[PDB]
Image (cartoon, coloured by chain):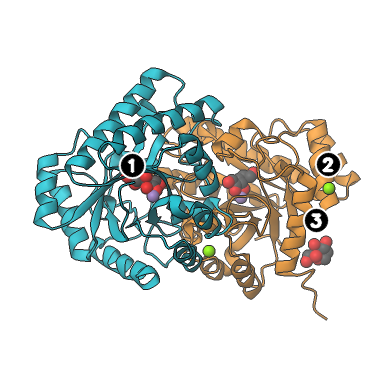
Chain colours: A orange, B cyan
Amino acid sequence: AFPKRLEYGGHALVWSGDWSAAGARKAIAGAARAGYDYIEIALLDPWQIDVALTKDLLQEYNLRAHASLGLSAATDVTSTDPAIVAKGDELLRKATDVLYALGGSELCGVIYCALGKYPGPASRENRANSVAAMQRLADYAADKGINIDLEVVNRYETNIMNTGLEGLAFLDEVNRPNAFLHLDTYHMNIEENGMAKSVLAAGDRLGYVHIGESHRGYLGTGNVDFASFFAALKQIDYRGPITFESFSSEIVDPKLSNTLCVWRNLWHDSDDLAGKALEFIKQRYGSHHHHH
Amino acid sequence: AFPKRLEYGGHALVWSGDWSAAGARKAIAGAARAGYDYIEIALLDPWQIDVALTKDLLQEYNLRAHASLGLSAATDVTSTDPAIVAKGDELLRKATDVLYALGGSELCGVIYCALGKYPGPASRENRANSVAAMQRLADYAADKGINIDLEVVNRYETNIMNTGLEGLAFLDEVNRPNAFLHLDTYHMNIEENGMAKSVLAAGDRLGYVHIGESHRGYLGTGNVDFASFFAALKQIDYRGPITFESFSSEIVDPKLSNTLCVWRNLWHDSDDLAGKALEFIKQRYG
Ligand SMILES: O=C(CO)[C@@H](O)[C@H](O)[C@H](O)CO
Ligand SMILES: O=C(CO)[C@@H](O)[C@H](O)[C@H](O)CO
Ligand SMILES: OC[C@@]1(O)OC[C@@H](O)[C@@H](O)[C@@H]1O
Ligand SMILES: [Mg+2]
Ligand SMILES: [Mg+2]
Ligand SMILES: [Mn+2]
Ligand SMILES: [Mn+2]
């Protein structure tokens, strides 16, 4: 395991649908402006990233970076097609290389399967291929001081693991020093037996957090029991990344907005949403955790 | 409109993945033994139901029936192609006919679009075609003293209506007295600003309720705020069908279970789940 610190992230996709020169600048400037410690860069296509330009921008804004992605049907490491698993391996190595180049230490999100609605349940073949892919990725990332955090998502976005407990069982199979659970309040709201159970069960194996409202709009305008979730995080003395995310159909790649089934926009202004979200998060977890 | 009474139902998929002679008996006997007033039959293929056998079982067990379904790509009444809308109209008429023969008064669920993940956002044309289809369905059902209840479901299951407010707006355009809102606590848990707003807004227009936990397993073992929901039902003095709805990966209808992404075995004992669900509901809304 590589060091984790309590730090707050803005998801790049809150501001920008791509990583063009303008997209990269807009998103980094947005996260910085809202008072975030880091930007979570979406590496769904890590060959699109101008790494030299991106590091220049991170320096310009004195902002740190972590990365998340979801695989696609063409790169699905669950695939019963060995060539597709290998294409996933290749995409994950490239994402790791980009994250490494930017001084980042966390690769998280749906890195263990294709993000989206599977037409049927996973076989132990899908599960075995995913675990082995996450072992090869963990081993590749380990030389680069990078932790991988496997994001548990709801039934409509994966068939592999939908609860923290399923995530921990999967990680028992991965059995790598730098592999962690990643929990997301939006997904937890659907799948979990309360918001505290998987956090308390995970303890030190919780490596990454996403904050989203039940409908992925403004924090506190939906059904997520944030009070319960953040009470659990405080109990385990969680000192790692916490990213705010939401997905506007006016900003994101139609590929993603259609996969996430974003049919209505709950907000217009990236800056207002992200600023209010961090205020809300720091109200729940505190300004800081520094003790004399 | 045909009267609504406070009655408690169990969804067929609590007991049975099909409506074979064996599946029908198992579901109807299960609902009767748990103490439900009615079984909610999943009529995704209303041509498959042996109506004469089902009537015999309902009478044998002294159990009433309502029906729910989802349309598919083949029957999607939001389609811009009249050939697909026509097939949807036909399936909805057949479902109404089966419900009539079984003495049921409620056709509910995702009757206004294909159940599942749309590849992109709905056009005003998709919406207008669905409204017109529900006008034709309402008119057909009205002749048979059958109410239709349009079920608001989450973003991954429709692109037409994901909130009670969107539901009420759609019904304003349908403008039929036997067309009602159908709310489901599982779907509300995702899409709604709390569990009260949509219920209070709907009032007399709320015609059918589904009680589902956040993960669709045992009631009271998830994130659904049932206290706020049932408080809102009391506020509007709701007297209508209340169905317990639950899905496990070990009781499967190959279409419906996969469409709903039921990946987990959240229960194995149907009788235990259904008995405890009915007690849970009656404790909160006797
Ligand atoms: O929760 C989600 C998707 O519902 C995002 O965090 C997603 O996993 C993606 O990896 C972000 O880049
Ligand atoms: O909530 C749902 C779908 O998520 C059910 O009400 C569905 O319409 C019914 O199972 C059809 O039989
Ligand atoms: O608790 C984390 C935090 O508030 O600690 C003090 C500063 O390092 C901040 O940038 C940081 O977000
Ligand atoms: Mg502003
Ligand atoms: Mg809740
Ligand atoms: Mn997330
Ligand atoms: Mn339902």
Q: Is residue B261 visible?
A: no
Quarter of the rendered structure image containing ligand 3:
bottom right
Indicate if the residue with disc 3 has its beta carbon within 8 Å of ligand 3. Answer: yes
Amino acid type assigned to the residue bearing label 1 in the image: Leu
Does residue B33 appear to the left or right of A54 in the view shown?
A: left
Pointer 2 indicates a residue of which chain? A
Does mark 3 fall on the same chain as mark 2?
yes
Q: Residue at x 36, y 29 (%)?
A: B136
Residue lying farthest to the bottom in this orientation: A292
Amino acid type assigned to the residue bearing label 2 in the image: Lys
Question: Circle 2 sits on which residue?
Answer: A55
Q: Residue at x 35, y 28 (%)?
A: B75
Q: Position of residue B3 (x, y in %)?
A: 31, 52
Does mark 3 fall on the same chain as mark 1?
no
* B222 or B163: nearer the viewer: B163
* A115 or B61: nearer the viewer: B61
Q: Position of residue A238 (x, y in %)?
A: 66, 68
Does residue B241 appear to the left or right of B175 in the view shown?
A: left
Indicate if the residue with disc 1 has its beta carbon within 8 Å of ligand 2. Answer: yes
SS class, disc 2: helix
Q: Which mark is residue A37?
A: 3
- Tell me how far mark 1 sits from mark 3, CA to CA: 44 Å
Does residue A244 appear to the left or right of B168 in the view shown?
A: right
Q: Residue at x 55, y 32 (%)?
A: A87
Question: Circle 1 sits on which residue?
Answer: B256
Q: Quadrant of the C terminus of chain B?
A: bottom left
Is disc 2 in contact with disc 1, using a CB cutoff of under 8 Å? no
Amino acid type assigned to the residue bearing label 3 in the image: Asp
Q: Position of residue A58 (x, y in %)?
A: 84, 45
Q: Which quadrant of the structure image shows residue A264?
A: top right
Relative height, residue B206 to residue B284 (above, below): above
